[PDB]
C-alpha cells in the first residue's frame, strides 16, 4: 500500500507527483523529499488498497523530465524515535537525519514519539545505530527500527513496585503515553517492595517504547521494566 | 533459497528430512530442531537454487508420518552472537536460547578444536519475532565475566561496512597490527590510514566485506589495544 | 572549615543552634535537618575561621536539653547532582534522598547543578551509588561525590570536532555552564572530522560535570569528551 | 598506620628504606616504586603501631642523600580492581596504571581481584575513572576506590530468582568469591519468577564487587543484583 519513488526531477512538488500518479486510485498521503546531493527528488506515496499501489509499480523505469524513475514497495524503512526535547519540531528531526547523511522521506509527530520513513532498509538500521543514545539538551535520544505485526514482544514486566504503586490506574496513566494498552495484569494478593505487574500493549513498538520506564522514578521507587518471558 | 519445515514427526533426523526433500532440487544444508514442548521437530533446508525452495513449499499441508507439516520461506530469522566463554559449545548456545523459550533452528560455530580468535556463532530461529526477541533478551548478558553481544543479521554501498578507529598513538598506527587486531571479526576489504598524522588523535578507517563483520568489530570500542583505549564507531556515510 | 552537630533536641530551631554556638566565632551559615526517624536534629555550621570550628568541637559530648551532642569536622560528605528536571526545587531533591533514607544536611541550588551535604561519608557514596543514572521525566540523573582541591582531573579533551566547531567562543558558551573555565586550548593548524580541543576547568568537579557533554550533539556532530591524559 | 614517603633517591631499595625508618617503630611491610620519569622513588611503609607511623611523619622534609623527602599518612589511596583476564599478573596490572601515567605503589594479587595502592587521592579517583569499563580480551574491567569502615553498603538484594535458584547453598557458592559472607537471608515461603534473597557481606568492598552479578546468568536465569535500601 506504500510506494517509494526514486530519481524525479528536482523541480517536483507534492502536486506534480500527485498529478502524475492520480490514475492509480485513491491516495491518502503524498510526501516529497530532496535527495542527498539535492540534484533529484524522492517521493513517498501511500495508497488506498494493495492494487492501488501495484499500479504505481507498473510505472517503474519510466522517463519523467529527463530522469528515468524507479518505483518500488516501501518496505522495512520505518523507525520510531523518542525522548527528544519537547521544543523539537519536525525540522529538528530532519536536521538530525541530515547530520548523518540520511534522507527523511516522511516524519509524523503528534511522552511523545515520532515515526520516520527513510529511503532504504540500510538507512533505517544505520540511523538507529548512529543516533540511539545521542544526548540533546540533557535528553538521551531513543530510537529503534519499527517492529511490524504472539504476546511475544508486546508484554512487559514491571518490578520493584511498593504496595502503594500496585495500582491499576497509576500504571495505566504512567504507561499510556507509549501506545495503546490492551491489558494490565496484577497478580493476586502481593500483600519487600518486590511487587510486580504485567502490561500487554497492542503493538510491539509500544512495548519497546515502554522499556524507557526501566531505571525510572515512579512515585518514590526506582522501577524495573523488561520484556516478559514468553509462555512455555 | 532456505526453507522452514514445521511439525515434523518427533523422530525425524537430518537423513529422513533429506530423503523426503531431495527430490525438490539440490540441497545444500539440512538442520533439524526440537520444538519447545518436544512433541515435534522443525527443520531448516537450504537449497542450491530458488526453485528447489519453491518445490519444497509445494509440500506444505502434506502428511509426513502422522503429522501435517507446514513449509515456508525462511527470511530475516538470522542472528549472530559472540563474546561468549571460549569453552562454550553449540549445546551451551542452544541452552541459552532455551532459557528464553526460543527454538534454535541451527547454530553454526567454529569448533573448540580451532580455538578461533574473536569467535562468533550464526544462529537461525523459527520466526522474525524470535530473532528480535532473542537479541533483546540476551544482549549484555554476563556469562563468566564476558558481556554477551548479539545482533540480528544485516544482509547485503560502504554504508555499515566501514568503521573509524580513533585515539590511536603513532606506534599503534600500523596496518599489520590493525589487520591482526580486527581480522577475527570477519573479512577485511581495505585498511585506510590517512597520511600526515605522525596528540594521540590518530585514526584509521577499516572497510569490511559485509556489515555484520563491521558490526562485530564495534566490540573494539572502549577496549585496550597495545597501551591505549581505542574508540570504534561506524564511519559517517559519504554525501 | 565546617562542623557537623549530631543529636540536638528536635525542638532545636536554626536560631537556637546559632545562639548556642555564636560564642565560637563569626558564623557564615547554619543549616538544620531532621533525623530519619525525626527524633533528634543535625546541624551544619560553617565558620569564618578554623579555630571557630575547633571551638565548636570542644562543645562535643556537652549536654544540650537532655541530649548529649556530638560535634566533628564535616569532611567528605559533599556531592553534586545535575540533569534533574528544570521544574525541580530544593524540596524535590530532599524527597529523592528521603526515598533512599538519607538525610540532606543542606542543599544549595543556584545547566543547573546542586551541591548537597549529608551526615556521613558512607551516605555520600551510597547516595551516588543509588541515584546516578536514575531516569526522572526522561532526564537521566547525574551524581558524583565532590572532589576536593595539578591539571589532573580538571582537564578535558573534546574530540570528533569539525573545522566549523573548532571555535574558542562556541566551546566557551557550550561549557561555561559546568563551572569556571581557566583555559581553552585549541592546537594550531588542525584545519576527516576528527579535531580536538583541550579545556581546563578551575576545579575538578566542573571537569567531571563537563563529561556529560560526551556523546552529545554539538551543533551538528556527536562530540566525545573525556578526562585528558596526564602529562608524564 | 601506613605511611607514604616521596622523593627518596632513585637508588633506594626497600632495604635502605627500612634502615632509615627502623628507629620509628616496628615495621610490617616495605614497598618501593619508581617515580613516573624514574628520577626518584616512592615508598609505602606499614608500621605495626600508630605511633610508629606518627614518628615517621616527623621525618618529612628531611634530606636523605640529596633529596628532600616528604612523609605523610597514606590515606584513601586504595582501589580494588577485578574482571581482568585470568592470565593477568601483577606486572600486567602495573602496565595498566603505567598506560595512564599513574604510579602503582603496591599491588596485592592473590574471580580474583586485586588491591592497588597509589600515591595520591587524585590518582585513585583518576585511575578508576580511566580504567573502569575498559575491555581487555572481552572482559569488561571493574574498579572502584576502596570503601573503608552498619548494614549500609554491605547488603545486596538478589531478584529474578526461580524456585530452583532459591537455595542458601548455590547462593553461597556463587557469591563467596567476592569476599566473606556474613549472612544469607531468604524470606520464607516464596513457592512469579520474582523470588529474592538478601546477602550481607563483612565489608562494603565485597558487596560492591558482588554487584557484578547483576544482569548475569545464574543457572538458567538472568539475575538482578543491587544495594539493599537502608532500613527506615
Image (cartoon, coloured by chain):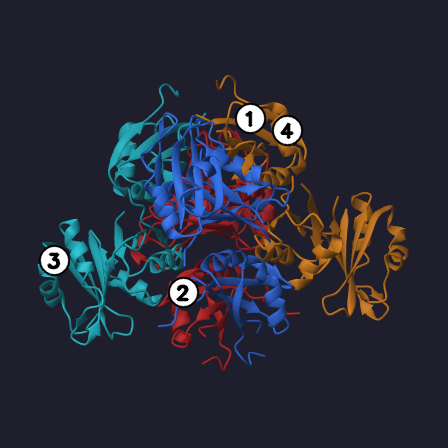
Chain colours: A orange, B red, C blue, D cyan
Q: Residue furthest front?
A: C23
- Tell me the distance, in whole angstroms, between the alpha carbons under discs 1 and 3: 62 Å
Residue topped by disc 2: C152
**Residue D185 visible here:** yes
Q: Mark 2 packing: few (<14 Cα in 10 Å), some, or many (20+)?
A: some
Q: Is residue C228 above or below residue B42?
A: below
Circle nearer the viewer, 1 or 2: 2
- Tell me the distance, in whole angstroms, between the alpha carbons under discs 2 and 3: 34 Å
Q: Are marks 1 and 3 in contact (CB under 8 Å)?
A: no
Q: Is residue B146 above or below residue A202?
A: below
Q: Position of residue D113 (x, y in %)?
A: 27, 50
Circle nearer the viewer, 2 or 3: 3
On whether disc 1 and disc 4 are found on a single subunit, the reply is: yes
Q: Mark 3 packing: few (<14 Cα in 10 Å), some, or many (20+)?
A: some
**Residue B13 visible here:** no
Q: Is residue C90 above or below residue D66?
A: above
- Tell me the distance, in whole angstroms, between the alpha carbons under discs 1 and 4: 11 Å
Residue in the foreground of this view, choosing between C37 and A135: C37
Circle nearer the viewer, 4 or 2: 2
- Tell me the distance, in whole angstroms, between the alpha carbons under discs 4 and 2: 49 Å
Q: Position of residue B48 (x, y in %)?
A: 53, 55
Q: Are marks 3 and 4 in contact (CB under 8 Å)?
A: no
Residue topped by disc 3: D24
What is the quadrant of residue A167 in the picture? top right
Q: Secondary structure at mark 1?
A: loop
Residue topped by disc 1: A165
The dot on residue A172 is 4
Q: Mark 4 packing: few (<14 Cα in 10 Å), some, or many (20+)?
A: some
> In the drawing, does residue D167 fall left or right of residue B4?
left
Amino acid at each position: 500500500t506504500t510506494v517509494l519513488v526514486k530519481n524525479l526531477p528536482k523541480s517536483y512538488n507534492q502536486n506534480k507527483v500527485y498529478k502524475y500518479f492520480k490514475h492509480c486510485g485513491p491516495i491518502i498521503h503524498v510526501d516529497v523529499a530532496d535527495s542527498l546531493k539535492k540534484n533529484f527528488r524522492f517521493a513517498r506515496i501511500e495508497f488506498a488498497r494493495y492494487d492501488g499501489a501495484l499500479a504505481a509499480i507498473t510505472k517503474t523505469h519510466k522517463v519523467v523530465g529527463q530522469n528515468e524513475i524507479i518505483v518500488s514497495h516501501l518496505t522495512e524503512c520505518t523507525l520510531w524515535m523518542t525522548n527528544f526535547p519537547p521544543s523539537y519540531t519536525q525540522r529538528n528531526i530532519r536536521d538530525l537525519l541530515q547530520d548523518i547523511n540520511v534522507v527523511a522521506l516522511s516524519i509524523r509527530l503528534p511522552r511523545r514519539f515520532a515515526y520516520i520513513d527513510v529511503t532504504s532498509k540500510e538507512d533505517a538500521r544505520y540511523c538507529v545505530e548512529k543516533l540511539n543514545g545521542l544526548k540533546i539538551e540533557g535528553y538521551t535520544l531513543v530510537t529503534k527500527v519499527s517492529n511490524p505485526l504472539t504476546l511475544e514482544g508486546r508484554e512487559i514486566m514491571i518490578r520493584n513496585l511498593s504496595t502503594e504503586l500496585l495500582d491499576e490506574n497509576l500504571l495505566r496513566e504512567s504507561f499510556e503515553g507509549f501506545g495503546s494498552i490492551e491489558k494490565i495484569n496484577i497478580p493476586a494478593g502481593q500483600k519487600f517492595n518486590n511487587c510486580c505487574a504485567f502490561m500487554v500493549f497492542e503493538n510491539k513498538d509500544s512495548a519497546e517504547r515502554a522499556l524507557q520506564m526501566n531505571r525510572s522514578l515512579l512515585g518514590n521507587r526506582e522501577i524495573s521494566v523488561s520484556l516478559a518471558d514468553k509462555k512455555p
